[PDB]
Length: 390
Ligand SMILES: N#Cc1ccc(COc2cccc(C3CCN(Cc4nc5ccc(C(=O)O)cc5n4C[C@@H]4CCO4)CC3)n2)c(F)c1
Image (cartoon, rainbow, N blue to C red):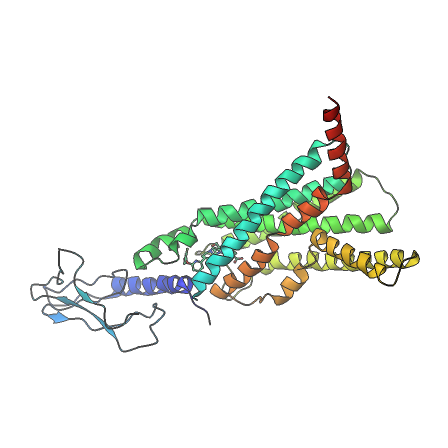
């Protein structure tokens, strides 16, 4: 098992709840001058009769609570009925030496750096490429409208991750103490957190459905008779941008109705997460079938012509390498490797490694379909000649 500050704070909440109930349920002692019973962030202490110490068990929410189940934090209140103050009139004296004491926090922090750098390169390249394809009016096709909508989905996905990471400053808090935990929990069960999470989910799903729109349009070019060019464009834009909403708002409704705490992370017993994960896998699988059929087409067209025994393979390899980025073919591997029953730190480590590799899909697409594209080079030359004549 892997544990981090995540699981420690999540157990702290349950400890606090039980402690609050006990404090609110414990009858007061019959005697007087008793030392008042309070919950400090570190531990919960009961009432103590004056002139004696308190023998409390080591709190179970600590990661090292199982190493020594024999320690006892000690706090003393004098015979007058007040806790013993320590030096410089500070928090009352307590004995913490009984039970006290690379990591998952470090791993997650490095993956975040690689994924942020990749998304930031992808964002910049896709903005340049959208400028280039929208600018020139000779490059106005239907396939270039599909490409612009795909670029838009990539850019929205990158922009959503930055907001989620910047709104909850987890990287700075990776070493927070007990006091800092209260705040962390307060933001998690707020409404800003839940709606920022919902926005990120929508942007992920919309990107996936624009790599299926790409695939379905190429397939219909290679296997179908020409049909109305507006009745197909409206249908494609509708599928790309508004089919995600048919399973992202039902998920956001069930989560909002049937949950009190948390920022809508994966529930404990029930599995609501299938409302999002299941259509994503459907799109990924259909787009894999499209990939295989298109490559079969290229192989027959390549065998029919006259080439060597090796030039066939060279051109086939180059074409397959150039088509993995457009249809997102690697997501079939990355969905095979991912464990769908992991929760907490393990889930975050797995997710971040996939994001670390797949953050640079937008950069690959931008280079392959806008910077080395032959027509784009052609307009750069033609535009340059008109200025050089002047
Ligand atoms: N309580 C609390 C708490 C505890 C510790 C710390 C600081 O230390 C640690 C330690 C381990 C991991 C982390 C961060 C690692 C991840 N981020 C934020 C975050 N990105 C997510 C992406 C996808 C999903 C998903 O399920 O698909 C869910 C995602 N989540 C967690 C929830 C979801 C909204 O936020 C949250 C923390 N930070 C703290 F900042 C808060």
